[PDB]
Amino acid sequence: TTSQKHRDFVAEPMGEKPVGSLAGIGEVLGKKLEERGFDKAYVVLGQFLVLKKDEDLFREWLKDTCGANAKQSRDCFGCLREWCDAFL
Amino acid sequence: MTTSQKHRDFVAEPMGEKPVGSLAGIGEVLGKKLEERGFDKAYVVLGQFLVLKKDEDLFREWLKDTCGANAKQSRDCFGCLREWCDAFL
Image (cartoon, rainbow over all chains, first blue to last red; front, side):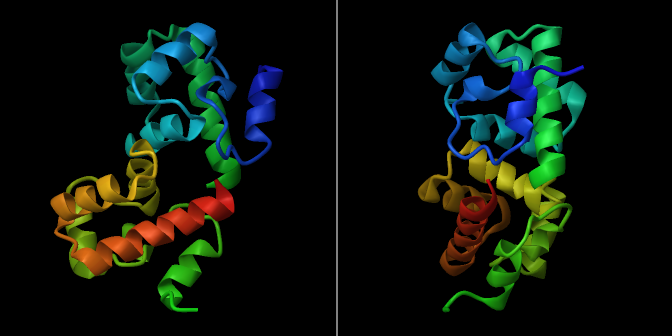
């Protein structure tokens, strides 16, 4: 199942949306991502793409980078995967 | 229009699974070196462009270091990704 946050993200180009528009990325995760350079959703999309959309490696990278738990990283992965299926 | 037809074809549509050689500036020689470093689909190079926050200097220097692109090749590749993003991201 999906959140409305997920459905809102996958419905449209992400443009300059902040990293916190990604499903799973709340205030705490978003702050830690911004501190490490990932201030916009497209920067995280970039890492997803550099990693060739690999679920295990992306979710592990996200845990290592901002401390996402398994649900948060699952949510973030799935919203980027569905966004790419629609727009890339 | 001063862009290549190859730029125009790339920016006209989502890139999907297009190979790296569909990018403007990326001929067969650069495309092979990119593929050997893991950058086998155009979207992987898009990924690097985005991870570098679309910065021209960083992206063009990365392309030079990774496949030996010259100034014109790196400018063309950057401009193609920049216009693609303006259209579709």
